[PDB]
Image (cartoon, rainbow, N blue to C red; front, side):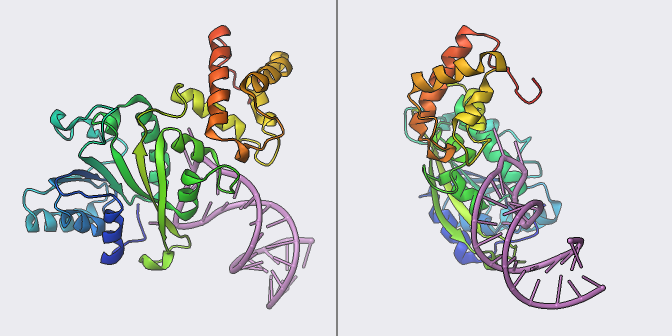
Length: 293
RNA sequence: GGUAAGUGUACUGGAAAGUGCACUUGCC
């Protein structure tokens, strides 16, 4: 539940500029409380604004706008996590993948406790081209915490280079655009808020299943300041770990003295592609959870 | 020594913050 509100008509209006030209668009907004952005979206001449809101306190104020803008704002009382936007718009709007993005957009100012699990849920959806991505390469404009925004957009060798960097950037073009200060919200939180734009890639930079990249990225990054080989080890049961780790790094041409923050997405394609071949040869390797064995 | 803030720093795929460490400022 949200307890810090963005109501500056200057900042909500600037968020919807960064989403692009929406002048006949079908927009799905997830966050809206006081509808600050909601008002900003409707003044952009969208075709429809679909809006989901769990908190009932905000729905009378959203109806306030479904009448000041008749035939423009569809309201839904619901949970953005259970809600299926795959069926919220017509099949006529579905563009192919190797086309341009569709006329469907996601804009969102969720609580960070909702938006952080959800961006990963949506990243898996991009992988499977289902979910919000039945329409094609649906773009999304979301608010994360200043720090989380930088991790999604971080390049190699930087300090915010985390798991979220690779899980996002291999599937999406990611632009951390600007950062609103906490003082602009009401009441003020003890954090700053970043704004990030996602555009799904026609060809992902790793073509492996999402759960496979997940596992490689999770193990590379689990020991954070150390040699990246400290983490890649744990993909392999102890009995084969010495030989399977050396074979992994050598075939992928990875320097084991590299740190997790130093590995390009190219390095992950090589690690993932070779790890994919190891699981094809040993059908019971992929399930090795080192945490107990 | 115990404690609580603040600052810096490290980490977080469950970040409107949290935790470790260092220093500073107060207190017991």
